[PDB]
Amino acid sequence: TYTQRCRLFVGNLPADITEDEFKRLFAKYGEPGEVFINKGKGFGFIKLESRALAEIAKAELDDTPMRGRQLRVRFATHAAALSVRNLSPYVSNELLEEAFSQFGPIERAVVIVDDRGRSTGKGIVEFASKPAARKAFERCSEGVFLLTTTPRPVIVEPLEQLDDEDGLPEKLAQKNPMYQKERETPPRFAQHGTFEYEYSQRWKSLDEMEKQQREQVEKNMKDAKDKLESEMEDAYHEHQANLLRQDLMRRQEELRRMEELHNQEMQKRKEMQLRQEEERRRREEEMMIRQREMEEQM
Amino acid sequence: TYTQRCRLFVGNLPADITEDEFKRLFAKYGEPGEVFINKGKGFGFIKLESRALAEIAKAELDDTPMRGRQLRVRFATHAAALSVRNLSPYVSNELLEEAFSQFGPIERAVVIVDDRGRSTGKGIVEFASKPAARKAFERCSEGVFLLTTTPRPVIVEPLEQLDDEDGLPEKLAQKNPMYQKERETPPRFAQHGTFEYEYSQRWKSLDEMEKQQREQVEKNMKDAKDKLESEMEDAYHEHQANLLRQDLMRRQEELRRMEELHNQEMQKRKEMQLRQEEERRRREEEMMIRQREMEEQMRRQ
Image 1: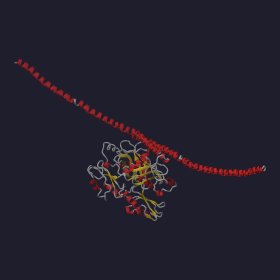
Image 2 (image 1 turned 120 degrees about the horizontal axis):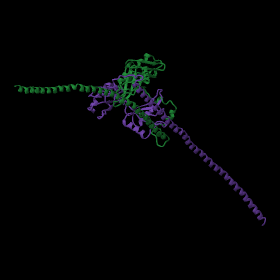
Image 3 (image 1 turned 30 degrees about the horizontal axis):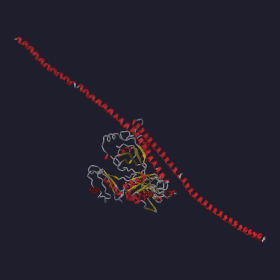
Image 4 (image 1 turned 60 degrees about the horizontal axis):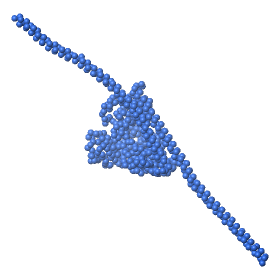
Protein backbone atom coordinates (compact mmCIF):
# COMPACT_ATOMS: atom_id res chain seq x y z
CA THR A 1 0.00 0.00 0.00
CA TYR A 2 0.95 3.67 -0.35
CA THR A 3 2.97 2.84 -3.46
CA GLN A 4 4.41 5.42 -5.86
CA ARG A 5 1.48 4.43 -8.08
CA CYS A 6 -0.99 6.12 -5.74
CA ARG A 7 1.29 9.13 -5.29
CA LEU A 8 -0.21 12.38 -6.60
CA PHE A 9 0.96 15.88 -7.62
CA VAL A 10 -0.85 19.17 -6.93
CA GLY A 11 -0.10 22.27 -9.00
CA ASN A 12 -1.27 25.93 -8.87
CA LEU A 13 -1.18 26.06 -5.03
CA PRO A 14 -1.31 29.60 -3.44
CA ALA A 15 2.11 30.99 -2.34
CA ASP A 16 0.79 31.24 1.32
CA ILE A 17 0.17 27.43 1.65
CA THR A 18 1.07 25.46 4.83
CA GLU A 19 1.81 21.72 5.29
CA ASP A 20 -1.35 20.95 7.38
CA GLU A 21 -3.52 23.09 5.01
CA PHE A 22 -2.37 20.90 2.07
CA LYS A 23 -2.93 17.50 3.82
CA ARG A 24 -6.50 18.58 4.81
CA LEU A 25 -7.73 18.57 1.15
CA PHE A 26 -7.16 14.79 0.84
CA ALA A 27 -8.28 13.91 4.44
CA LYS A 28 -11.78 13.03 3.18
CA TYR A 29 -10.32 10.16 1.16
CA GLY A 30 -8.40 8.20 3.79
CA GLU A 31 -5.03 8.81 5.43
CA PRO A 32 -2.13 10.98 4.21
CA GLY A 33 1.20 9.21 3.70
CA GLU A 34 4.37 10.84 2.30
CA VAL A 35 4.06 14.64 1.88
CA PHE A 36 6.43 17.00 -0.02
CA ILE A 37 5.40 20.62 -0.78
CA ASN A 38 7.47 23.42 -2.38
CA LYS A 39 5.48 26.51 -1.20
CA GLY A 40 7.66 28.92 -3.25
CA LYS A 41 7.03 27.42 -6.73
CA GLY A 42 3.59 26.28 -5.51
CA PHE A 43 3.60 22.49 -6.10
CA GLY A 44 3.05 19.55 -3.74
CA PHE A 45 3.21 15.73 -3.61
CA ILE A 46 0.95 13.32 -1.66
CA LYS A 47 1.15 9.53 -1.16
CA LEU A 48 -2.32 7.92 -0.85
CA GLU A 49 -3.20 4.40 0.50
CA SER A 50 -4.48 2.86 -2.79
CA ARG A 51 -4.61 3.81 -6.51
CA ALA A 52 -8.44 3.63 -6.01
CA LEU A 53 -8.40 6.67 -3.62
CA ALA A 54 -5.89 8.36 -5.99
CA GLU A 55 -8.55 8.22 -8.78
CA ILE A 56 -11.23 9.63 -6.38
CA ALA A 57 -8.89 12.50 -5.25
CA LYS A 58 -8.13 13.73 -8.83
CA ALA A 59 -11.81 13.46 -9.99
CA GLU A 60 -13.05 15.65 -7.08
CA LEU A 61 -10.10 18.02 -6.40
CA ASP A 62 -8.88 19.07 -9.90
CA ASP A 63 -9.51 22.74 -10.96
CA THR A 64 -11.08 23.34 -7.47
CA PRO A 65 -10.87 26.91 -6.02
CA MET A 66 -8.23 27.69 -3.37
CA ARG A 67 -7.51 31.38 -2.58
CA GLY A 68 -8.15 32.54 -6.16
CA ARG A 69 -5.86 29.96 -7.85
CA GLN A 70 -7.51 26.88 -9.50
CA LEU A 71 -5.54 23.79 -8.30
CA ARG A 72 -4.06 21.24 -10.73
CA VAL A 73 -4.28 17.78 -9.12
CA ARG A 74 -2.47 15.28 -11.40
CA PHE A 75 -0.96 11.76 -11.03
CA ALA A 76 2.74 11.68 -10.04
CA THR A 77 5.14 9.70 -12.29
CA HIS A 78 6.89 6.58 -10.91
CA ALA A 79 10.56 7.71 -10.58
CA ALA A 80 11.57 4.28 -9.12
CA ALA A 81 10.35 2.26 -12.20
CA LEU A 82 12.62 0.43 -14.63
CA SER A 83 12.40 -1.60 -17.85
CA VAL A 84 13.63 -5.19 -17.99
CA ARG A 85 13.89 -7.37 -21.10
CA ASN A 86 15.50 -10.53 -22.42
CA LEU A 87 13.29 -12.66 -20.16
CA SER A 88 12.32 -16.35 -20.49
CA PRO A 89 8.57 -17.14 -21.14
CA TYR A 90 8.76 -19.20 -17.91
CA VAL A 91 9.69 -16.03 -15.88
CA SER A 92 6.82 -14.93 -13.55
CA ASN A 93 5.92 -11.62 -11.76
CA GLU A 94 6.64 -13.32 -8.38
CA LEU A 95 10.09 -14.63 -9.56
CA LEU A 96 11.05 -11.15 -10.92
CA GLU A 97 10.01 -9.67 -7.51
CA GLU A 98 12.16 -12.39 -5.79
CA ALA A 99 15.03 -11.54 -8.19
CA PHE A 100 15.20 -7.73 -7.83
CA SER A 101 14.34 -7.75 -4.05
CA GLN A 102 18.13 -8.05 -3.33
CA PHE A 103 18.82 -4.49 -4.66
CA GLY A 104 16.06 -2.79 -2.62
CA PRO A 105 12.37 -3.13 -1.63
CA ILE A 106 9.96 -3.93 -4.51
CA GLU A 107 6.60 -2.10 -4.69
CA ARG A 108 5.27 -3.90 -7.84
CA ALA A 109 7.06 -6.16 -10.39
CA VAL A 110 5.08 -7.19 -13.53
CA VAL A 111 6.00 -9.29 -16.60
CA ILE A 112 4.20 -7.92 -19.73
CA VAL A 113 1.96 -10.53 -21.46
CA ASP A 114 0.19 -10.46 -24.87
CA ASP A 115 -3.66 -10.50 -25.43
CA ARG A 116 -3.71 -14.34 -25.76
CA GLY A 117 -1.80 -15.05 -22.51
CA ARG A 118 1.82 -15.69 -23.65
CA SER A 119 4.75 -13.66 -22.20
CA THR A 120 6.51 -10.80 -24.10
CA GLY A 121 10.05 -11.12 -22.66
CA LYS A 122 9.80 -7.57 -21.22
CA GLY A 123 9.12 -6.68 -17.58
CA ILE A 124 8.43 -3.68 -15.30
CA VAL A 125 10.41 -3.38 -12.03
CA GLU A 126 9.10 -0.60 -9.73
CA PHE A 127 11.05 0.11 -6.50
CA ALA A 128 10.10 1.59 -3.08
CA SER A 129 13.02 4.06 -3.41
CA LYS A 130 14.89 5.73 -6.33
CA PRO A 131 18.53 4.94 -5.14
CA ALA A 132 17.59 1.19 -5.04
CA ALA A 133 16.74 1.41 -8.80
CA ARG A 134 20.00 3.35 -9.60
CA LYS A 135 21.96 0.59 -7.72
CA ALA A 136 20.03 -2.21 -9.58
CA PHE A 137 20.80 -0.47 -12.92
CA GLU A 138 24.59 0.01 -12.32
CA ARG A 139 24.99 -3.60 -11.07
CA CYS A 140 23.16 -5.05 -14.15
CA SER A 141 24.68 -2.67 -16.79
CA GLU A 142 28.34 -3.42 -15.86
CA GLY A 143 27.85 -6.86 -14.26
CA VAL A 144 25.62 -9.81 -15.27
CA PHE A 145 22.33 -10.75 -13.53
CA LEU A 146 20.34 -13.98 -14.11
CA LEU A 147 17.10 -15.74 -13.09
CA THR A 148 16.59 -19.21 -14.62
CA THR A 149 18.84 -22.26 -15.10
CA THR A 150 19.64 -21.31 -18.78
CA PRO A 151 22.22 -18.41 -18.83
CA ARG A 152 19.83 -15.88 -20.54
CA PRO A 153 20.98 -12.37 -19.34
CA VAL A 154 18.69 -9.56 -18.06
CA ILE A 155 19.02 -6.01 -19.51
CA VAL A 156 17.71 -3.32 -17.12
CA GLU A 157 16.73 -0.07 -18.91
CA PRO A 158 15.20 3.21 -17.53
CA LEU A 159 11.40 3.17 -18.10
CA GLU A 160 10.23 5.58 -20.85
CA GLN A 161 6.98 6.86 -19.29
CA LEU A 162 4.38 8.30 -21.73
CA ASP A 163 1.72 10.99 -21.06
CA ASP A 164 -1.99 10.28 -21.58
CA GLU A 165 -3.71 12.77 -19.28
CA ASP A 166 -1.96 16.05 -20.06
CA GLY A 167 -0.61 16.30 -23.60
CA LEU A 168 -0.66 19.60 -25.47
CA PRO A 169 -3.87 21.66 -25.57
CA GLU A 170 -4.71 24.63 -27.88
CA LYS A 171 -4.99 26.94 -24.77
CA LEU A 172 -1.28 26.56 -23.99
CA ALA A 173 -0.18 25.82 -27.55
CA GLN A 174 -0.99 28.94 -29.57
CA LYS A 175 1.91 30.82 -27.98
CA ASN A 176 4.18 30.82 -31.04
CA PRO A 177 4.15 32.93 -34.19
CA MET A 178 4.76 30.16 -36.73
CA TYR A 179 1.50 28.82 -35.29
CA GLN A 180 -0.20 31.40 -37.51
CA LYS A 181 1.55 30.22 -40.68
CA GLU A 182 1.13 26.50 -39.74
CA ARG A 183 -2.50 26.74 -38.52
CA GLU A 184 -3.59 28.92 -41.50
CA THR A 185 -4.53 25.79 -43.55
CA PRO A 186 -7.12 23.44 -41.90
CA PRO A 187 -6.83 19.57 -42.03
CA ARG A 188 -7.69 18.06 -45.46
CA PHE A 189 -6.87 15.22 -47.93
CA ALA A 190 -4.24 16.25 -50.56
CA GLN A 191 -4.96 16.59 -54.34
CA HIS A 192 -2.80 15.00 -57.13
CA GLY A 193 -0.10 16.93 -59.04
CA THR A 194 0.37 19.72 -56.42
CA PHE A 195 3.82 20.88 -55.11
CA GLU A 196 2.59 19.65 -51.66
CA TYR A 197 1.49 16.22 -53.06
CA GLU A 198 5.07 15.47 -54.33
CA TYR A 199 6.44 15.58 -50.72
CA SER A 200 3.31 13.66 -49.50
CA GLN A 201 4.43 10.67 -51.69
CA ARG A 202 8.26 11.15 -51.74
CA TRP A 203 8.51 11.36 -47.90
CA LYS A 204 5.85 8.62 -47.34
CA SER A 205 7.94 6.15 -49.42
CA LEU A 206 11.07 7.06 -47.34
CA ASP A 207 9.20 6.04 -44.12
CA GLU A 208 8.07 2.74 -45.78
CA MET A 209 11.80 2.30 -46.67
CA GLU A 210 12.86 3.37 -43.10
CA LYS A 211 10.41 0.99 -41.31
CA GLN A 212 11.64 -1.90 -43.53
CA GLN A 213 15.38 -1.00 -43.21
CA ARG A 214 14.78 -0.67 -39.40
CA GLU A 215 12.93 -4.06 -39.34
CA GLN A 216 15.82 -5.40 -41.52
CA VAL A 217 18.35 -4.79 -38.64
CA GLU A 218 15.76 -6.26 -36.15
CA LYS A 219 15.58 -9.67 -37.96
CA ASN A 220 19.31 -9.41 -38.95
CA MET A 221 20.32 -9.28 -35.25
CA LYS A 222 17.44 -11.60 -34.11
CA ASP A 223 19.00 -14.62 -35.93
CA ALA A 224 22.62 -13.56 -34.99
CA LYS A 225 21.67 -13.60 -31.25
CA ASP A 226 19.58 -16.78 -31.89
CA LYS A 227 22.90 -18.46 -32.95
CA LEU A 228 24.32 -18.01 -29.37
CA GLU A 229 20.79 -18.77 -27.98
CA SER A 230 20.44 -22.08 -29.92
CA GLU A 231 24.21 -22.94 -29.63
CA MET A 232 23.95 -23.10 -25.80
CA GLU A 233 20.37 -24.49 -25.69
CA ASP A 234 21.21 -27.33 -28.21
CA ALA A 235 24.91 -28.23 -27.56
CA TYR A 236 24.95 -27.61 -23.76
CA HIS A 237 21.92 -30.03 -23.67
CA GLU A 238 24.38 -32.64 -25.10
CA HIS A 239 26.58 -32.00 -21.96
CA GLN A 240 23.55 -33.17 -19.87
CA ALA A 241 22.99 -36.11 -22.31
CA ASN A 242 26.73 -37.10 -22.23
CA LEU A 243 26.74 -37.44 -18.39
CA LEU A 244 23.42 -39.40 -18.58
CA ARG A 245 24.74 -41.73 -21.37
CA GLN A 246 27.86 -42.38 -19.18
CA ASP A 247 25.53 -43.32 -16.26
CA LEU A 248 23.57 -45.68 -18.60
CA MET A 249 26.85 -47.38 -19.66
CA ARG A 250 27.93 -47.76 -15.97
CA ARG A 251 24.49 -49.15 -14.96
CA GLN A 252 24.55 -51.62 -17.95
CA GLU A 253 28.00 -53.09 -16.99
CA GLU A 254 26.69 -53.87 -13.43
CA LEU A 255 23.78 -55.95 -14.88
CA ARG A 256 26.11 -57.38 -17.62
CA ARG A 257 28.71 -58.72 -15.10
CA MET A 258 25.90 -60.15 -12.88
CA GLU A 259 24.48 -62.06 -15.92
CA GLU A 260 28.09 -63.40 -16.38
CA LEU A 261 29.38 -64.24 -12.83
CA HIS A 262 26.08 -65.26 -11.11
CA ASN A 263 24.72 -66.99 -14.27
CA GLN A 264 27.66 -69.50 -14.07
CA GLU A 265 26.38 -70.52 -10.57
CA MET A 266 23.24 -71.98 -12.28
CA GLN A 267 25.36 -73.45 -15.16
CA LYS A 268 27.74 -75.28 -12.73
CA ARG A 269 24.64 -76.38 -10.69
CA LYS A 270 23.31 -78.27 -13.79
CA GLU A 271 26.75 -80.05 -13.93
CA MET A 272 26.06 -81.57 -10.45
CA GLN A 273 22.59 -82.74 -11.70
CA LEU A 274 24.29 -84.36 -14.76
CA ARG A 275 26.90 -85.91 -12.37
CA GLN A 276 24.09 -87.47 -10.20
CA GLU A 277 22.44 -89.00 -13.35
CA GLU A 278 25.87 -90.49 -14.27
CA GLU A 279 26.26 -91.72 -10.63
CA ARG A 280 22.91 -93.68 -10.46
CA ARG A 281 23.57 -95.50 -13.79
CA ARG A 282 27.16 -96.39 -12.66
CA ARG A 283 25.66 -97.66 -9.33
CA GLU A 284 23.43 -100.06 -11.37
CA GLU A 285 26.47 -101.19 -13.48
CA GLU A 286 28.46 -102.01 -10.26
CA MET A 287 25.47 -104.03 -8.91
CA MET A 288 25.17 -105.88 -12.28
CA ILE A 289 28.97 -106.63 -12.45
CA ARG A 290 28.74 -107.99 -8.82
CA GLN A 291 25.63 -110.13 -9.67
CA ARG A 292 27.45 -111.61 -12.75
CA GLU A 293 30.00 -112.97 -10.20
CA MET A 294 27.23 -113.87 -7.64
CA GLU A 295 25.62 -116.19 -10.28
CA GLU A 296 29.09 -117.80 -10.78
CA GLN A 297 29.65 -117.78 -6.93
CA MET A 298 26.63 -120.18 -6.62
CA THR B 1 -20.47 7.22 -18.88
CA TYR B 2 -20.40 3.83 -20.59
CA THR B 3 -17.21 4.69 -22.47
CA GLN B 4 -14.29 2.55 -23.64
CA ARG B 5 -12.24 3.29 -20.52
CA CYS B 6 -15.20 2.04 -18.47
CA ARG B 7 -15.26 -1.12 -20.70
CA LEU B 8 -13.97 -4.54 -19.46
CA PHE B 9 -12.46 -7.44 -21.49
CA VAL B 10 -13.43 -11.02 -20.63
CA GLY B 11 -11.56 -14.22 -21.50
CA ASN B 12 -11.20 -17.88 -20.59
CA LEU B 13 -14.87 -18.86 -20.76
CA PRO B 14 -16.47 -22.32 -21.06
CA ALA B 15 -18.71 -23.79 -23.85
CA ASP B 16 -21.92 -23.20 -21.74
CA ILE B 17 -21.99 -19.32 -21.94
CA THR B 18 -25.12 -17.83 -23.65
CA GLU B 19 -26.84 -14.40 -24.15
CA ASP B 20 -28.99 -14.89 -20.97
CA GLU B 21 -26.20 -16.34 -18.72
CA PHE B 22 -23.77 -13.44 -19.49
CA LYS B 23 -26.39 -10.75 -18.56
CA ARG B 24 -26.97 -12.19 -15.00
CA LEU B 25 -23.30 -11.56 -13.97
CA PHE B 26 -23.60 -7.88 -15.07
CA ALA B 27 -27.22 -7.53 -13.75
CA LYS B 28 -25.91 -6.76 -10.20
CA TYR B 29 -23.55 -3.97 -11.46
CA GLY B 30 -26.19 -1.21 -11.93
CA GLU B 31 -27.51 -1.65 -15.50
CA PRO B 32 -25.93 -3.54 -18.49
CA GLY B 33 -24.66 -1.46 -21.42
CA GLU B 34 -23.49 -2.87 -24.79
CA VAL B 35 -24.22 -6.66 -24.87
CA PHE B 36 -22.25 -8.56 -27.59
CA ILE B 37 -21.12 -12.20 -26.96
CA ASN B 38 -19.08 -14.42 -29.36
CA LYS B 39 -19.53 -18.25 -29.32
CA GLY B 40 -16.33 -19.40 -31.07
CA LYS B 41 -13.34 -17.87 -29.31
CA GLY B 42 -15.11 -16.51 -26.24
CA PHE B 43 -14.53 -12.79 -25.84
CA GLY B 44 -16.30 -9.41 -25.80
CA PHE B 45 -16.70 -5.83 -24.48
CA ILE B 46 -19.34 -4.30 -22.11
CA LYS B 47 -19.54 -0.60 -21.06
CA LEU B 48 -19.81 0.29 -17.33
CA GLU B 49 -21.41 3.23 -15.39
CA SER B 50 -18.03 4.90 -14.48
CA ARG B 51 -14.19 4.38 -14.48
CA ALA B 52 -14.09 4.09 -10.63
CA LEU B 53 -17.02 1.58 -10.55
CA ALA B 54 -15.36 -0.41 -13.41
CA GLU B 55 -12.22 -0.98 -11.23
CA ILE B 56 -14.43 -2.57 -8.47
CA ALA B 57 -16.03 -4.95 -11.07
CA LYS B 58 -12.46 -5.65 -12.39
CA ALA B 59 -10.78 -6.80 -9.09
CA GLU B 60 -13.79 -8.75 -7.67
CA LEU B 61 -14.59 -10.86 -10.79
CA ASP B 62 -10.88 -11.64 -11.52
CA ASP B 63 -9.47 -15.14 -10.68
CA THR B 64 -12.92 -16.48 -9.56
CA PRO B 65 -13.69 -20.23 -10.10
CA MET B 66 -16.47 -20.65 -12.70
CA ARG B 67 -16.85 -24.15 -14.30
CA GLY B 68 -13.09 -24.89 -14.57
CA ARG B 69 -11.38 -21.96 -16.37
CA GLN B 70 -10.50 -18.85 -14.29
CA LEU B 71 -12.24 -15.58 -15.32
CA ARG B 72 -9.64 -13.20 -16.86
CA VAL B 73 -11.31 -9.81 -16.41
CA ARG B 74 -8.37 -7.40 -16.73
CA PHE B 75 -8.37 -3.75 -17.81
CA ALA B 76 -9.90 -4.28 -21.25
CA THR B 77 -7.34 -2.83 -23.67
CA HIS B 78 -8.56 -0.01 -25.91
CA ALA B 79 -9.19 -1.51 -29.35
CA ALA B 80 -9.09 0.44 -32.62
CA ALA B 81 -6.40 2.62 -31.02
CA LEU B 82 -4.07 4.29 -33.55
CA SER B 83 -0.64 5.86 -32.90
CA VAL B 84 0.18 8.78 -35.20
CA ARG B 85 3.80 9.70 -35.88
CA ASN B 86 5.52 12.60 -37.65
CA LEU B 87 3.47 15.49 -36.29
CA SER B 88 4.15 19.22 -36.66
CA PRO B 89 5.17 20.83 -33.32
CA TYR B 90 2.15 23.13 -34.02
CA VAL B 91 -0.53 20.35 -33.70
CA SER B 92 -2.73 20.42 -30.54
CA ASN B 93 -4.99 17.88 -28.69
CA GLU B 94 -8.14 19.77 -29.85
CA LEU B 95 -6.85 20.05 -33.47
CA LEU B 96 -5.97 16.30 -33.64
CA GLU B 97 -9.44 15.43 -32.20
CA GLU B 98 -11.30 17.42 -34.92
CA ALA B 99 -8.95 16.10 -37.68
CA PHE B 100 -9.58 12.37 -37.07
CA SER B 101 -13.35 12.92 -36.50
CA GLN B 102 -13.71 13.08 -40.37
CA PHE B 103 -13.67 9.23 -40.50
CA GLY B 104 -15.72 8.41 -37.36
CA PRO B 105 -16.33 9.28 -33.66
CA ILE B 106 -13.24 10.02 -31.49
CA GLU B 107 -13.30 8.98 -27.79
CA ARG B 108 -9.90 10.48 -26.76
CA ALA B 109 -7.12 12.48 -28.48
CA VAL B 110 -3.69 13.30 -26.98
CA VAL B 111 -0.46 14.77 -28.46
CA ILE B 112 2.60 13.22 -26.70
CA VAL B 113 4.60 15.86 -24.76
CA ASP B 114 8.31 15.63 -23.83
CA ASP B 115 10.09 16.27 -20.44
CA ARG B 116 9.88 20.08 -21.08
CA GLY B 117 6.16 20.08 -22.11
CA ARG B 118 6.92 20.59 -25.85
CA SER B 119 5.69 18.45 -28.83
CA THR B 120 7.45 15.12 -29.57
CA GLY B 121 5.93 14.73 -33.06
CA LYS B 122 3.81 11.71 -32.01
CA GLY B 123 0.17 11.42 -30.86
CA ILE B 124 -2.52 8.96 -29.67
CA VAL B 125 -6.03 8.69 -31.20
CA GLU B 126 -8.84 6.64 -29.54
CA PHE B 127 -11.51 5.49 -32.08
CA ALA B 128 -15.05 4.53 -30.96
CA SER B 129 -15.88 2.02 -33.75
CA LYS B 130 -13.92 -0.76 -35.55
CA PRO B 131 -14.97 0.15 -39.21
CA ALA B 132 -14.04 3.87 -38.75
CA ALA B 133 -10.41 3.00 -37.74
CA ARG B 134 -10.20 0.56 -40.74
CA LYS B 135 -11.36 3.36 -43.13
CA ALA B 136 -8.95 5.84 -41.41
CA PHE B 137 -5.99 3.56 -42.26
CA GLU B 138 -7.46 2.87 -45.78
CA ARG B 139 -7.44 6.66 -46.51
CA CYS B 140 -3.71 6.72 -45.50
CA SER B 141 -3.03 3.49 -47.51
CA GLU B 142 -4.15 4.54 -51.04
CA GLY B 143 -3.94 8.33 -50.56
CA VAL B 144 -2.79 10.92 -47.95
CA PHE B 145 -4.13 13.02 -45.01
CA LEU B 146 -2.55 16.39 -44.09
CA LEU B 147 -3.19 18.60 -41.03
CA THR B 148 -1.01 21.74 -41.42
CA THR B 149 0.26 24.20 -44.12
CA THR B 150 3.69 22.45 -44.43
CA PRO B 151 3.10 19.05 -46.18
CA ARG B 152 4.04 16.86 -43.18
CA PRO B 153 2.24 13.50 -43.76
CA VAL B 154 0.54 12.13 -40.63
CA ILE B 155 1.90 8.53 -40.56
CA VAL B 156 -0.95 6.52 -38.96
CA GLU B 157 0.30 3.33 -37.24
CA PRO B 158 -1.82 0.63 -35.44
CA LEU B 159 -1.23 0.92 -31.66
CA GLU B 160 -0.32 -2.34 -29.85
CA GLN B 161 -2.27 -2.86 -26.61
CA LEU B 162 -0.45 -5.20 -24.19
CA ASP B 163 -1.55 -6.50 -20.74
CA ASP B 164 0.59 -4.63 -18.16
CA GLU B 165 -1.61 -4.93 -15.01
CA ASP B 166 -2.32 -8.70 -14.56
CA GLY B 167 0.90 -10.22 -15.99
CA LEU B 168 1.99 -13.87 -15.60
CA PRO B 169 1.45 -15.12 -11.97
CA GLU B 170 2.36 -18.59 -10.55
CA LYS B 171 -1.33 -19.16 -9.49
CA LEU B 172 -2.38 -19.51 -13.18
CA ALA B 173 1.04 -20.59 -14.63
CA GLN B 174 0.84 -23.68 -16.91
CA LYS B 175 2.76 -26.93 -16.15
CA ASN B 176 5.42 -28.32 -18.55
CA PRO B 177 8.79 -30.21 -18.01
CA MET B 178 10.87 -27.02 -18.61
CA TYR B 179 8.59 -24.85 -16.32
CA GLN B 180 9.85 -26.83 -13.25
CA LYS B 181 13.44 -27.46 -14.58
CA GLU B 182 14.40 -23.75 -15.05
CA ARG B 183 12.89 -22.89 -11.60
CA GLU B 184 15.41 -25.26 -9.86
CA THR B 185 18.17 -22.57 -10.07
CA PRO B 186 17.50 -19.39 -7.97
CA PRO B 187 18.03 -15.85 -9.44
CA ARG B 188 21.83 -15.36 -9.30
CA PHE B 189 24.65 -13.02 -10.27
CA ALA B 190 27.25 -14.35 -12.69
CA GLN B 191 30.86 -14.66 -11.43
CA HIS B 192 34.03 -13.37 -13.19
CA GLY B 193 35.58 -16.00 -15.48
CA THR B 194 32.59 -18.44 -15.46
CA PHE B 195 31.05 -19.77 -18.73
CA GLU B 196 27.53 -18.48 -17.81
CA TYR B 197 29.13 -14.99 -17.46
CA GLU B 198 31.12 -15.39 -20.74
CA TYR B 199 28.07 -16.39 -22.89
CA SER B 200 25.89 -13.59 -21.39
CA GLN B 201 28.66 -10.91 -21.75
CA ARG B 202 29.08 -11.99 -25.39
CA TRP B 203 25.26 -11.94 -25.80
CA LYS B 204 25.10 -8.39 -24.28
CA SER B 205 27.69 -7.41 -26.95
CA LEU B 206 25.17 -8.42 -29.68
CA ASP B 207 22.66 -6.01 -27.98
CA GLU B 208 25.39 -3.25 -27.99
CA MET B 209 25.69 -4.13 -31.73
CA GLU B 210 21.86 -4.04 -32.26
CA LYS B 211 21.69 -0.62 -30.49
CA GLN B 212 24.51 0.86 -32.68
CA GLN B 213 22.85 -0.58 -35.84
CA ARG B 214 19.54 1.12 -34.77
CA GLU B 215 20.99 4.47 -33.50
CA GLN B 216 22.90 4.83 -36.81
CA VAL B 217 19.90 3.77 -38.98
CA GLU B 218 17.76 6.37 -37.09
CA LYS B 219 20.21 9.24 -37.88
CA ASN B 220 21.16 8.19 -41.48
CA MET B 221 17.40 7.94 -42.36
CA LYS B 222 16.56 11.25 -40.60
CA ASP B 223 19.28 13.13 -42.63
CA ALA B 224 17.89 11.60 -45.88
CA LYS B 225 14.41 12.88 -44.85
CA ASP B 226 16.01 16.21 -43.70
CA LYS B 227 17.59 16.69 -47.17
CA LEU B 228 14.16 16.06 -48.83
CA GLU B 229 12.76 19.01 -46.76
CA SER B 230 15.38 21.47 -48.15
CA GLU B 231 14.89 19.97 -51.68
CA MET B 232 11.19 21.06 -51.56
CA GLU B 233 11.20 24.13 -49.23
CA ASP B 234 14.18 25.98 -50.86
CA ALA B 235 12.69 24.94 -54.26
CA TYR B 236 9.33 26.55 -53.22
CA HIS B 237 11.07 29.78 -52.01
CA GLU B 238 12.61 30.03 -55.54
CA HIS B 239 9.28 29.00 -57.21
CA GLN B 240 7.22 31.62 -55.23
CA ALA B 241 9.53 34.37 -56.62
CA ASN B 242 9.49 32.73 -60.14
CA LEU B 243 5.64 32.79 -60.14
CA LEU B 244 5.78 36.40 -58.77
CA ARG B 245 8.20 37.31 -61.67
CA GLN B 246 5.51 36.00 -64.12
CA ASP B 247 2.91 38.51 -62.74
CA LEU B 248 5.68 41.19 -62.45
CA MET B 249 6.60 40.76 -66.19
CA ARG B 250 2.82 40.80 -66.97
CA ARG B 251 2.58 44.09 -64.98
CA GLN B 252 5.84 45.33 -66.67
CA GLU B 253 4.57 44.71 -70.26
CA GLU B 254 1.23 46.29 -69.05
CA LEU B 255 3.04 49.68 -69.00
CA ARG B 256 5.20 48.96 -72.13
CA ARG B 257 1.81 48.53 -73.94
CA MET B 258 0.41 51.68 -72.17
CA GLU B 259 3.48 53.79 -73.16
CA GLU B 260 3.69 52.45 -76.79
CA LEU B 261 0.03 53.35 -77.63
CA HIS B 262 0.53 56.72 -75.84
CA ASN B 263 3.65 57.11 -78.07
CA GLN B 264 1.56 56.09 -81.17
CA GLU B 265 -1.05 58.74 -80.16
CA MET B 266 1.76 61.31 -79.48
CA GLN B 267 3.21 60.49 -82.96
CA LYS B 268 -0.36 60.99 -84.33
CA ARG B 269 -0.98 64.37 -82.48
CA LYS B 270 2.20 65.66 -84.21
CA GLU B 271 1.35 63.97 -87.58
CA MET B 272 -2.12 65.69 -87.56
CA GLN B 273 -0.53 69.17 -87.15
CA LEU B 274 2.28 68.33 -89.66
CA ARG B 275 -0.35 67.67 -92.38
CA GLN B 276 -2.35 70.75 -91.21
CA GLU B 277 0.74 73.02 -91.79
CA GLU B 278 1.25 71.37 -95.24
CA GLU B 279 -2.38 72.02 -96.39
CA ARG B 280 -2.84 75.51 -94.82
CA ARG B 281 0.53 76.51 -96.37
CA ARG B 282 -0.35 75.12 -99.86
CA ARG B 283 -3.60 77.18 -99.71
CA GLU B 284 -1.48 80.39 -99.28
CA GLU B 285 0.61 79.19 -102.27
CA GLU B 286 -2.55 78.17 -104.28
CA MET B 287 -4.19 81.61 -103.78
CA MET B 288 -0.86 83.35 -104.69
CA ILE B 289 -0.32 81.63 -108.11
CA ARG B 290 -4.00 82.05 -109.21
CA GLN B 291 -3.62 85.80 -108.45
CA ARG B 292 -0.30 86.23 -110.36
CA GLU B 293 -1.58 84.05 -113.29
CA MET B 294 -4.56 86.42 -113.83
CA GLU B 295 -2.10 89.40 -113.56
CA GLU B 296 -0.05 88.40 -116.68
CA GLN B 297 -3.29 87.19 -118.37
CA MET B 298 -4.87 90.69 -117.98
CA ARG B 299 -1.58 92.38 -118.87
CA ARG B 300 -2.05 90.94 -122.36
CA GLN B 301 -5.70 91.54 -123.27
